[PDB]
Image (tube, rainbow, N blue to C red; front, side, top):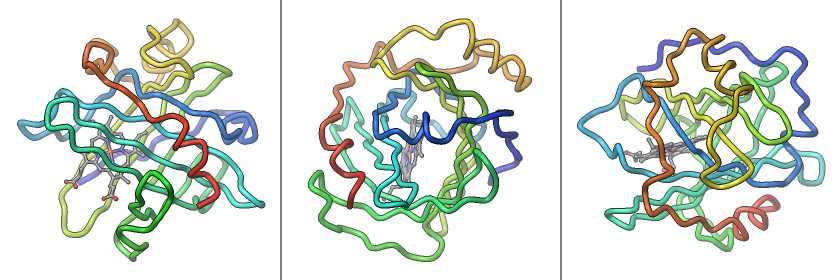
Length: 184
Ligand code: HEM
């Protein structure tokens, strides 16, 4: 179960974050892991599509090769804090698993600038027991985390040394499909 009420960035610039470009997860902190894929890859695109906040997601397990895509409309709770009911889609946006109540994640942008971000998410999927996940994002795949986002990790009272890197994972990303999924 999740335990954190993440605080959104003061002065969060929604149009800059939700600009249609891709964010790569470079490092993450799961407060409730199991044995787990310590090795894992994720990226998202965040945009506005004909006046709706949207996110497209891409997950790739570099060992199992398990790959899946999602699209969500984000509903606003407050500036920088959203609730996202997701649908699993193929890369072209065709629905594989419809939106359903109880399949949602929350999404809080704790820090963002033009290149980097720190987010919190709490995923709810069926009767699954999931915990808090923090992710360091970058516009450039595998970029080393800079001092602004690392300071934000510290300011959240987290230890960056505890985050797991995705940079050494033989990750590959379908960023073109993320971009096009925004409309789906
Ligand atoms: C910004 C970040 C993230 C968001 C918003 C996110 C969102 C989601 C969503 C919506 C699902 C369910 C998709 C579906 O069933 O249609 C999912 C599943 C999953 N995610 Fe992520 N995720 C993110 C980052 C990560 C990271 C970095 C990892 C590596 C720890 C991760 C590992 C997983 C796994 C293992 C599942 C499968 C859950 C299950 O079905 O048992 N995710 N995620």
